[PDB]
Length: 140
Length: 139
Image (cartoon, rainbow over all chains, first blue to last red):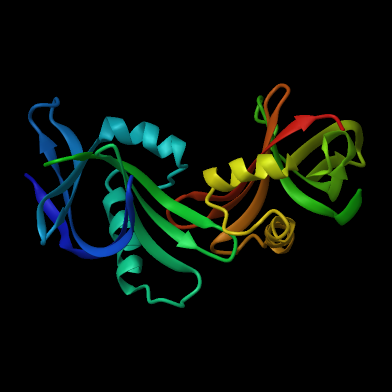
C-alpha cells in the first residue's frame, strides 16, 4: 500500500568533503506505506536522486517506532500521520524561496564519507535555523 | 566589565518535579576582557531573581567558546555582534502575547547543577529553539 505523496525536483545546496558548495536540482520522492518485513509497521520513506547522475542516491526510512524518538528530540507537536505533510510544506518553501527574501528557507544535503545529513533551514540575520534534520543512507 | 543589557524577562522555569512557573527573571549581559587569560574577550550572562537570593545562574562565553557554539548552531555573526542578537531574541519573549502564532517564549530548564536556557518558537509543527545555552549555578 505504498503511496507517493510527493515526487518532483527541489533546489538543494549540496556539500561534500572535498568539494565546494553546489546548488542543484535534486529529485525528492516521499512515500508512506507498510513494510511486511518489519511487523507491518507504518513507514515514511524519502529518496533523493539526481536526473544527471544516476548513482547519486540517498534514502531514508522512518517507522512509527522510529518517529517516537525523533519526535522527542526535535520537539515535534504533530503525529506520525501528519509528519510527511509538514516535510512537504517545508520543501514547498524551499521551492518558492527566491534570493533576497529574508528569512529564506532552503534545503541542504551534507555528505560525509558517503553517508549524508539532510536539513531544511530558515536563514535569518542571526543563524541557520534547522526546522528539520534527517540522516540519509547512500543508495536506494 | 561592562553591562550591555539589564532587564527583567518572562521565563518559563522548568525543574524536575515539573514545577512550571512563569516568573520574571532578571537578566544581566556583560562583555569584558579577561585579565588572567591574556585579554581573551568574555561574554557573561547572569540570571537572577529578586524573590530568591539563592536563585543564581551564570554563563560565560569566551571567544573560543563562541567559535564552538557558532559551529553547532550555525551562527552567522561574529562574537561582537552576538550579544545584539540575544537581546533581540529576549525582546521577542518580553513582548510575546498568549494569542501569538508563532509564539516566542524563554525557557530555563534546571537539572541538578547545570541548567539549560532556550528561546523557542512554537509554530504549527514544533518547538523550534532559536538559541540554546548551558548555564551553571552561582555567580
